[PDB]
Image (cartoon, rainbow over all chains, first blue to last red; front, side, top):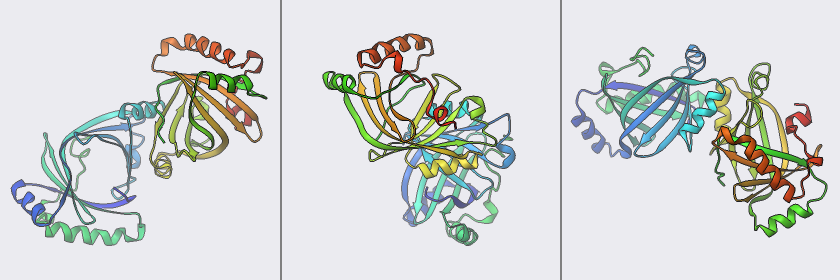
Length: 175
Length: 178
């Protein structure tokens, strides 16, 4: 986290033993490990933000205790977040503005770093094991170049186009 | 600097032209000077033709210097409703709010001092056009005790020499015409 823009590639994980072998070998640093994460998705009037390709999430990470208010979009390559003190409080603030819980997504999540690359290891119940590879930038001009780098890095990680999942978590759940 | 908050804020505002009793009372009760003489910049955000204002809602990004207090505030609808959150990065939250449709509508600047006597927040304000004001407020998570907390505020105000004579119930935005 530090960058308005990002490219991300998301992948199904068939084998977590080999993933964790790449993480040791790449000398990734562990940010957070096996957190329970709860994402409250919020929207006005059924679908006001959904319709502009924006998602707004109130996210809590347990046991790390990270609390984030996140605006994703418009589209796939835009995302900004703020660290918040109190999820219940920001929720009520946004409710006053007319944003109400649309649905929730829960997951288990670990976050690793390899230089500028974030590796996120996800497990959802209704779906399975995922990895997400992402780089962020504040430079709008570099975004197109980050696409090639993110692809090259993922391949290095043994996570190739054949195992790619281009559907978001909210799409995979019909939300 | 972090400020600790609530859901409702019961508040009485007064125009003041000397602060003798108020100063004497702060000293006598050994008031906590939370921060004194801060420059405070309030960026009021709104959508479209003033959609928030049209709901009796104000939404503010507040910075205070030198304390470095940074707050995201939703005021209303109306009267006693007020919720606030410490934020780390004003430009970030401003950028996120813009993606939602909220954009700066106007700014209000003030000099502000903040004191605590127990649950009472004492605020002393100077605004360029308007003059000097003092507010006594209490916050609460209890909607049912509002009028009782009004009487408590009134009693306190009077002990501080702030008389009903001087009361200014209009908000700063209302006094400026914004």
